Amino acid sequence: QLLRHYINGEFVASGTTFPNLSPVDGRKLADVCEADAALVDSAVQAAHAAQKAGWRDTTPAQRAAWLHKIADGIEARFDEFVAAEVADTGRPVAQARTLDIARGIANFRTFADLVRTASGEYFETHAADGSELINYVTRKPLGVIGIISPWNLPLLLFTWKVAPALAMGNCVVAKPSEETPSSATLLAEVMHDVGLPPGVFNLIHGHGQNAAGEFLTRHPDISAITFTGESRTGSTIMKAVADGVKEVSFELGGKNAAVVFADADFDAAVAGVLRSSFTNAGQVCLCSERVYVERPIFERFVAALKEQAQALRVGAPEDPATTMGPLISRGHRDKVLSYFRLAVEEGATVVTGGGAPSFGDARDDGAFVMPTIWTGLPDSARCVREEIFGPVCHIAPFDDEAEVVKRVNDSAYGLAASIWTTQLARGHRVAKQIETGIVWVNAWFVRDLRTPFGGTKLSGLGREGGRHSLDFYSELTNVCVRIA
Amino acid sequence: RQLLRHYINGEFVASGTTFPNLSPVDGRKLADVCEADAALVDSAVQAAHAAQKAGWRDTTPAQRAAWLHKIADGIEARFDEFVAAEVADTGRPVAQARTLDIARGIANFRTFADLVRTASGEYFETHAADGSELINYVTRKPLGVIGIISPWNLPLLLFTWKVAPALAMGNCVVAKPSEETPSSATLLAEVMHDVGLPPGVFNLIHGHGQNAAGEFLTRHPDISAITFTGESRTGSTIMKAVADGVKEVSFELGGKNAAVVFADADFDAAVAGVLRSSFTNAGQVCLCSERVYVERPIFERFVAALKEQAQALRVGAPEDPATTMGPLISRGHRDKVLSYFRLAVEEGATVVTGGGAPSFGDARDDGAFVMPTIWTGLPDSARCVREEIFGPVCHIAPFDDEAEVVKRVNDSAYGLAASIWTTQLARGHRVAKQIETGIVWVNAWFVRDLRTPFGGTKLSGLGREGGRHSLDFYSELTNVCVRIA
Amino acid sequence: QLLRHYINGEFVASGTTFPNLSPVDGRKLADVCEADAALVDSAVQAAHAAQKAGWRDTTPAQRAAWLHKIADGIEARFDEFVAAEVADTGRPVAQARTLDIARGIANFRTFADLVRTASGEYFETHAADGSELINYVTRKPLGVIGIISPWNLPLLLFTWKVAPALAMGNCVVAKPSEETPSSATLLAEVMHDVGLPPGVFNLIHGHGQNAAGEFLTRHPDISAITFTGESRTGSTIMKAVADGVKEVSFELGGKNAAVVFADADFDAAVAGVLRSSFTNAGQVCLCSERVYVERPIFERFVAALKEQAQALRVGAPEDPATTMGPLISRGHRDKVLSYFRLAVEEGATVVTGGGAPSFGDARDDGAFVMPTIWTGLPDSARCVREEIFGPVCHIAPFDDEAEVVKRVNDSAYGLAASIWTTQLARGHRVAKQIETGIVWVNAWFVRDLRTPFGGTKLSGLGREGGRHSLDFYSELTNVCVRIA
Amino acid sequence: RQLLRHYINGEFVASGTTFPNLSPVDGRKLADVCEADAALVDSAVQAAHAAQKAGWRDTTPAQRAAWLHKIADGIEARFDEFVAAEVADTGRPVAQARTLDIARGIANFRTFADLVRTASGEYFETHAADGSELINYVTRKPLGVIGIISPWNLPLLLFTWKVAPALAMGNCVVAKPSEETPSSATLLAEVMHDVGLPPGVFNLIHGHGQNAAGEFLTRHPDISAITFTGESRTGSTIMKAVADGVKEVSFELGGKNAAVVFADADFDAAVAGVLRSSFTNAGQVCLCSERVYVERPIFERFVAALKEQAQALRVGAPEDPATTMGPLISRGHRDKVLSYFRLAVEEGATVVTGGGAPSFGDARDDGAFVMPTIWTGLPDSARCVREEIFGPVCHIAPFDDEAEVVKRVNDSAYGLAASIWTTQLARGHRVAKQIETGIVWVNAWFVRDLRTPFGGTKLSGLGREGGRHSLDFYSELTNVCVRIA
Ligand SMILES: [Mg+2]
Ligand SMILES: [Mg+2]
Ligand SMILES: [Mg+2]
Ligand SMILES: [Mg+2]
Ligand SMILES: [Mg+2]
Ligand SMILES: [Mg+2]
Ligand SMILES: [Mg+2]
Ligand SMILES: [Mg+2]
Ligand SMILES: [Mg+2]
Ligand SMILES: [Mg+2]
Ligand SMILES: [Mg+2]
Ligand SMILES: [Mg+2]
């Protein structure tokens, strides 16, 4: 199998290639083409031309119909998409079916429905001099959107940017993670099979720094960059687009807290924190790596979570009993295991986990790590402040509400938080104080796609979802007409 | 000596070096201005951060709206002083400073006070796959500390355009006005002080930009956002400076704006309108029309009529009631403009009127005056019709058809604003919708409803301000998602 | 063929029947069942039960999916629906395809998309005493909607009320016009074939006063009545629901003006006024029966419209050359011909038309009338004030703008108006002065289904379209929760 | 003689018959009130219609907002007079008249002034089948003349709740206050006059309801709408009366509202809250809780605590600073309430406290006082727990589970409001969402954010007012659809 670029309506091979390797057993899955700067420029030019060749002038109804054809096209190959996603990431099959591919599909239908119903603002102005004017706000595409998408939830986070960009009449040059090329290449096959006009959607494969990703961010003819991934890489991109003052939309790192009050539903909160710590082997920007538990239930809470974490089954996705997969790569695992080392240096009590398992077969050539729980670290320790992006949480006691609010907000990140309580007043008054883009109460990672999603502080720039997506992927123009 | 001090944590404070504030009318020294170094800038940011936690963060919208109206009242109570400070710094004719600068400065505070008082939020119900139900609602809290760097061209107006929504949304502010125009911002600090706004909520720092107080502010790791109005090159520098902290940014940057006059336009209104859009504030507004396109059958008549009105302008000092155009901001800026005037001539321009400085024979010659200027004869590719000059000048070219002039207007790396003159219903709307700018006026110019989205496309900006766009920019949105079943 | 009621998931025959007769040649098309009060009560009870049996608790996603199944179901029988509509009304086939059945279908998809994207309002309250509350606005169904629909655009105006009522989770008891039963009965067959839960949609056939329509309006267990038809009948219904204070939504009569300024595009304005006067043989509440033309083009305008009106071909829909059909019935024709008589009594100049044609075959057993133009009547004449609802317009000269605005607004009706001008300022400043629910400039009967549609004065109560439909077919509840 | 006159077309005018205004505290005559016959009502409507065309129709939102703030200022300038008029008409304790009646009366004007100033509209683009393009925008103009019939229970508050949005949207008004409570509306007319509102924009007519001025107003063919707050039976009569003209209607009608107290509630807060929701204004608010349901484990303790607080109320005249509950509005209304008190006893109620009138031994006995009353022991089917009494009474019943009490609350032909007392997060939201009323409070009662939709379901109303709902009701929406290509 060879994974090719998709440029101006046709698949294209290129220069050097690199192998796509399984995080489960290290086996070679495919070769992947690597786009050089000339090839990236090729794609950007194809997208600019497709703008002028008529895509810019499609109606919202025409665009929504295209989005629904694409969504139909994914469904028709649903199992192919699942198998591709599982092979790239090692994600358990059941989770790939219901969280990854399904939500990938829902992204297209959601923005299709939103651009069909979307309207605009109208204002009447009565000027001091007695004149009268009308104002209305129109939208046109930015033009060409460059999309650099992350490896942790590959199809989901890719379609999350591609669907609204196309919905607002932009063309797209998209570069998926070098670790997870497969489902994006299948999406290109769908684009091709439904006959999207050539150059409207372009896929380029390759690496990031000094490679295709960078080239894309520095191209003078892109109109904006959308990015999900590490905060440091967000900063690099922000500098790269600066001279062209390009638009940017960032979803970056987090060091999210879960707070469990003594009045919580105890067994739901333990199950909830298990999910928010170890889903996708803790490789979700929304995962909870800090937990604060009110002191009277702190010891029992640690004990109960330890039991449930040790009952997880770490392994290959073809095993129906598997409930946590590997990390994305042995390189990422080296970074996570180095934090696990640092926790011991910082004096942590290792409640469970703290290393990689041993299988005694080809799974040892993969990238597995055990679910890990720490206690005993102060709020100042590097391991409770710095994002690890592995399956780990630290748990600490707290004594009162004003204290734990401050401890939650003590972070240079501000992506998400979850709070567990049964009390009406407490639930609302605590949630409104948390300096994050999202706060869940007695829940986690429930995503209504109409709501504003993004981060504060180091965790992001802008919001997506609903009208925030409509406004980001568009240029707003206020048309002000004198009528008297 | 008049000494213009910083305002930090509820008091005026000098610093260890100063620079002169000079009149653009006769070059005389008006004051000495303190210069904030990087340690003083950091002090202002920390005061702003402490003021957030000391309770400004927890004010209600009603409380904020009341503060903003008190501030508005305090400026009104000193209206003539504000006028005189603005006139002294900019040379702007008095009658215009009164009605466009200071009056709209006051209106910014009242407008955002009323918007925040009525603003509401969104609520969504979620029925999840597993049968559970959740409610979502979207809350806004302040970003925190907003850094505000404002330009010299409409000093009080554009300073308050940012300060008012920032304070309305419960942020604290560290604001650095232009080194050319410190005076009205300093009076604003006195008003803040006199109404007793809590210490640290509003901080004023004076100084220069590059390698000075402005730059220091943008690289500070504890600011939450930078709002900036000014040159596009400076926007790019700021964007890099905040990158490591991923700070929010809102930019209103350069433009090379066009006015389009169709043969079916109201001729007398379009000539007066283009006089206005070209020479208001001596052409020193980001929104000014430095390119004009006129449909060929009325082109010669249009050029001739505009020439006559432009030569009826009276260039001089603001104390003369007859003055209708003032100086440029500084002799340095005048040097840049007169260098473009020479470049237009090398590129083959016909000088219809103006093209140089007046000659007075007294101290007004020590100021920064230049004459209203009109060019013709340059191709769309010429530097003088592509590069922002930010002086009292327009180039006029003929066009033959509608599809053509739309292309010529959009052939620009800028995309701030445009104005179209026509009496035809279909034409007005269909042309306006194709223009790649943040704003398009039809039979008007620089009409600003503060509820509408204002900003630029391409090199001319990032984001929108006005109405809900200001409400959202100066706040962090939080979606609160609560399981109920 | 026998047209049956549809009650609680099954077709039901009833008591007496009446014939469905063609307006083209008088031939019998079918017998129609007639619902007595016990049968109407039967339907209302079935709808109330279906509310409690679970329809009230469907989600917006479930409802939208049902609406789309219904829309698919209509498309699958598109030609059957066209033939039924044409047979009932005599409408030309081409017009039945593109205006009637297509828009019937679009109504379902539109409200399906709107209830999927719809959201709600949230307000925070900071009370004087220092307390803090949140408010959010929820929607639940009214319950059971009684729908009485008109004969002029039968499927279109029926689905215009049925689609939003079902979208907001109501059950429906619907009574179509005794003149046009057929396409509504087919819609019931679609409801049945997709398996909508029993009692959610109920169809009752019969007449109005002292018959099924009245019975429905007086039932104590309906929650609201929606009605399109004559203003007098609106008043009767408003009185009938009064003791139960039921909700009402009315789209009633109009005496609409078209205004043509001398600066208009002359040939577009003549074509436009032909359309707005004689579409559906002038049997649309939106039709223009008054025209004001600026004096310098008044004589040429009358002459040009006369020529185009005489070029219309009045006849049976199976003739491909036919461009205007009959009136709905010989009874309605008697009322229209009595106004044509009154115009002569009032001193009108009859420019063209003024009577029924003669065919010399079975078409004389139908209900045809010729396109009719008058001049010479003062603003006070009954024939330019009272709604005729036939293919007629009166044309008058005017001299200035302020005059014609006043003459347009001089009416006890206020449904719609159209204005023809090429001038920017004039177009906007005149439109904003017109006391109607809708004003078109250089257009007529262009319906964006997201916009508010309804009348002022005698022409209506409420608006439908978009959020106005969402709010009408729902009960709003403000939930106010103290949190501190 | 004090004579209370109509206010029509900019002047006070008497009419040919009068009726006495009597105190509900001691029955003394306070004034004579003019009675408007059908010819005078028609005069007021024609004056209102002429004022529309004389230019009130063409005011801007800024102009209207300014009028509304002037009116608010004029009431404030006479605050103590308004208080004394309201107290004299209703017997309401002075401290409550000051903070709930007159203060909120003023706030209605300021609130709608700010809403209209910021309100905007919708814009839609249409791409039609034939390739043409159109723009749509939605404009609002006044309905025209609004007829306002207001109740006696919170006279100034509920009168201004309608007058302010009507005037804000550029309508003229013909308003008829209750024959029981004419005084504060007459002072409002004096304020209208003193600020110089144009003649015919605001008209006040006094008189009775059925076969009198109120009825005449509703049947007038030249009014555009009727807004009405009061009994459901009267709403039905009005609905028939406007039918021939298809007038707009907005109704806020009766209720038989419940308060629900779960065992997990904050006990002391819920007892105080139910005291409030039951006996505020002597139980004469449409929103009062006349049914209470308490979860069985705390039922007996709840009844006992409420009894003790109810017996600590002090029933008497408003000049006594110790008074905490006033009289009913009239001896006729008291007759209706005391007849329900007798009916409750026949239906088998246990009288926990109250059940009759106090006995003073002086002229207060000539007024309309009755004691706070609590019942238990009646089934859900009893007339005394189904029919609105509009006096200071509540019935309390036990319940055992959540699904049960939701059904009991919703078992009503009314559906105005409800309040729920619980400390549980999930319960608060899931119960509130099932209640079939226009409003549901959780741990609160009668908290009115004027931006939210306010109204009733079933027999309790038609339409919503508040925020955009008032903006839309008091305006005709016009969609303007313009072809541009
Ligand atoms: Mg790999
Ligand atoms: Mg549990
Ligand atoms: Mg945008
Ligand atoms: Mg200077
Ligand atoms: Mg932004
Ligand atoms: Mg924000
Ligand atoms: Mg028939
Ligand atoms: Mg033509
Ligand atoms: Mg409703
Ligand atoms: Mg009395
Ligand atoms: Mg209504
Ligand atoms: Mg309305």
Image (cartoon, coloured by chain):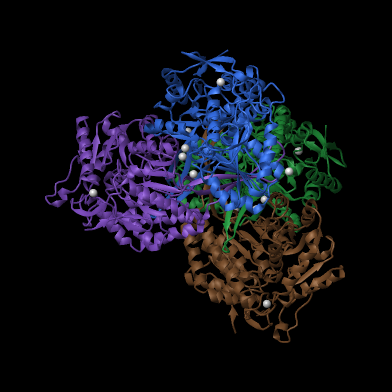
Chain colours: A blue, B purple, C green, D brown
Quadrant housing residue C90: top right
Q: Is residue C108 left or right of residue B400?
A: right
Q: Is residue D17 visible?
A: no
Closer to the camera in the image, C296 or C278: C278
Count every numbered label the image shows and give the total: 0
Quadrant housing residue B302: top left
Residue lying furthest bottom in this view?
D362
Residue D43: image location, x then y, percent: 58, 68
Residue C255: image location, x then y, percent: 60, 48
Quadrant housing residue D341: bottom right
Residue lying furthest left in this view?
B361
Q: Is residue B27 visible?
A: yes
Q: Is residue A479 left or right of residue C386?
A: left
Q: Is residue D221 left or right of residue B168?
A: right
Q: Quadrant of the N terminus of chain A?
A: top right
Residue at point 81% right, 55% down? D400
Residue A278: image location, x then y, percent: 63, 33
Closer to the camera in the image, B11 or D168: B11
- Vertical placement of residue A122 versus C129, above or below: above
Residue A140: image location, x then y, percent: 47, 34
Closer to the camera in the image, C298 or A467: A467
